[PDB]
Image 1: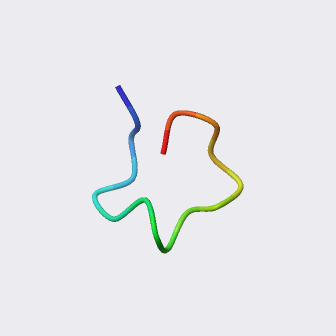
Image 2: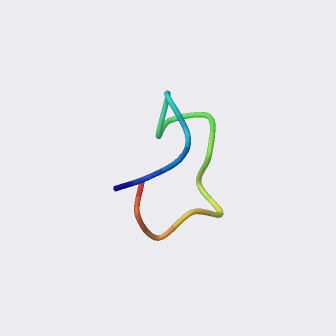
Amino acid sequence: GCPCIWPELCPWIRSC
């Protein structure tokens, strides 16, 4: 899954 806890703060992550 996305490594970033908050996907809203990690837009550069396709997972998020």
